[PDB]
Image (cartoon, rainbow, N blue to C red):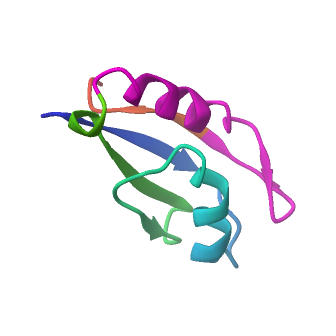
Amino acid sequence: GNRFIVFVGSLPRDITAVELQNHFKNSSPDQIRLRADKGIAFLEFDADKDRTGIQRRMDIALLQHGTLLKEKKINVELTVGG
């Protein structure tokens, strides 16, 4: 309902939660679940936490689309509404 999810993928085989937390630290996610099985993860963000702040939190997370992580390039897209 009052939350959105970030589809992050293409992650390295050796990925660590430390490297996930430090990336999205500024965007402040609610949920963090890494699935190395497909090199993807799920990051929920509580929209109810801030009606006018959830936007920037998503922007900051979305800006990581194509960033480099542990010598791999990763993707970031929306997941909820398609």
Which residue lies at the image location 74% right of the left edge and 37% below the top edge? 66
**Residue 10 makes an appearance in the image:** no
Tell me if 50 is positioned left or right of 32 in this view: left
Q: Is residue 48 left or right of residue 10?
A: left
Tell whether position 71 is magenta.
yes
State the residue lying farthest toward the right. Answer: 71
Is 48 situated left or right of 34 in this image? left
| As drawn, 68 above or below 78 | below
Circle count: 0
Q: Magenta stretch?
A: 51-75
**Residue lying at the far left of the rendered structure:** 1
Q: Quadrant of the N terminus?
A: top left
- Residue at 68%, 68% (x, y): give it: 19
Spot occupied by residue 79 in the image (x, y as percentages of width and height) = 35, 34
| Picture quarter with the C terminus | top left
The answer to whether residue 24 is visible is yes
Q: Tell me which corner region of the image, top left, top right, bottom left or bottom right, holds residue 72.
A: bottom right
Q: Residue at the spot x=77%, y=42% of the render?
A: 67
From the top left corner, tell me how far across and down residue 68 is, in percent.
81, 50
Residue 69 x %, y %: 78, 58
Which image quarter: residue 42? Answer: bottom left
Q: Position of residue 2 (x, y in %)?
A: 17, 33
Task: Please determine whether, in this image, residue 17 is positioned above or below residue 30.
Answer: below
Left/right placement of residue 47 relative to residue 69 reads: left
Any magenta on residue 3? no
Measuring 46% from the left and 43% from the top, which residue is drawn there?
A: 7
